Amino acid sequence: ISLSQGAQAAALLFSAAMDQISRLAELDIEPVRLPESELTGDSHSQHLLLGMEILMELYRQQHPDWTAPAIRQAFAPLARAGLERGYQEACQVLRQLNVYTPAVAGQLQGLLLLTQRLFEERLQIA
Amino acid sequence: ISLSQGAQAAALLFSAAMDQISRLAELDIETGDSHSQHLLLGMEILMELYRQQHPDWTAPAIRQAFAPLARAGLERGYQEACQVLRQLNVYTPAVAGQLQGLLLLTQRLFEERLQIA
């Protein structure tokens, strides 16, 4: 039942490549932040946010008729939903890989929470 | 080290979340398996964006340009993915072959895409 070790492989490739390419194509968008953010991210969260940026950006392009606010309004819950689900899937794989230690569970959780809040902040940028 | 398995759990969350969000937001263009599809949809998005960063260039002009960057991109990705899989002592003959499988396939499929449309 170890399609689980297939999933992990593919994820590693996905994440590394999306990085490498995004960098090489100079798509590397400067991380968008609240000028007075009290929060400090790490590279993991930063990767994640840059990811969500692209998704939003393309969502925007795909909805020309829609206003800027409506666009943020609509995209916000899908992004939250996507991330919480993403997380749930990432956890399942790890439980299944029998590597879901209390340490790793806590680190991954912290990362979700960090990312959610950072995105909440990003969405406030008018 | 804890360091590596972090980079792992992060990669999981990244991949999955990008998967989820792209589906939920209906970002799409209307043979393969999910892992390649995922990667493809990955690259198509990036290219699509890269397109928009050069409104002035022609369509072939951007395919010409983006292709090598996608190729170089995957290879690097693949190396880095082998790194962690080794660091974690979890790089089975089976796993390695599976991964190399996914590299080549994706790789080809993207080439077939460039010839199309």
Image (cartoon, coloured by chain):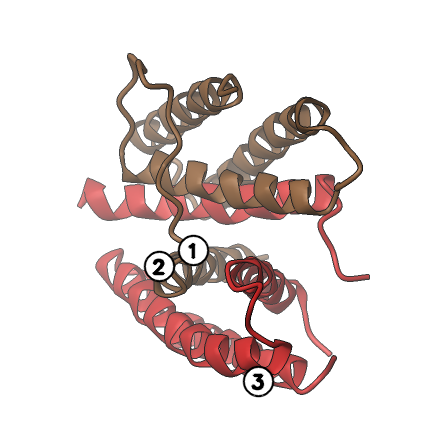
Chain colours: A brown, B red
Mark 2 and 1 residues: CB-CB less than 8 Å, in contact? yes
Say few, some or many: other residues with alpha carbon within 10 Å of mark 2 (under 14 / 14 to 19 / 20 or more).
Answer: some
Q: Chain of mark 3?
A: B
Q: Secondary structure at mark 1?
A: loop
* Protein chain holding label 2: A
Q: Residue furthest front?
A: B56
Location of residue A48 in the rendering, given as x and y in whole percent from the top left corner: 43, 39
Label 3 close to label 2 by CB (< 8 Å):
no
Element carrying mark 2 = helix
Mark 1 crowd level (few <14, some 14–19, many ≥20, 10 Å Cα): some
Residue marked by disc 3: B108
* Labels 3, 2: front one: 2
* Residue at 67% across, 46% down: A61
Q: Amino acid at mark 3?
A: Arg
Q: Nearer the viewer, residue B13 or A33?
A: A33
Q: Amino acid at mark 2?
A: Arg
Q: CA distance from mark 3 to mark 2?
A: 22 Å
Q: SS for tag 3?
A: helix
Q: Is residue A80 left or right of residue B92?
A: right
Disc 2 versus disc 1: nearer the observer = 1
Q: Reply above or below: B28 against B17.
A: below
Q: Nearer the viewer, mark 1 or mark 3?
A: 1
Which chain is disc 1 placed on?
Answer: A
Identify the image quadrant of the C terminus of chain B.
bottom right
Residue B64 x %, y %: 51, 83
- Same-subunit check for callouts 3 and 2: no
Q: Which residue is mark 2?
A: A23
Tag of residue A27: 1
Q: Residue B93's image quarter?
A: bottom left
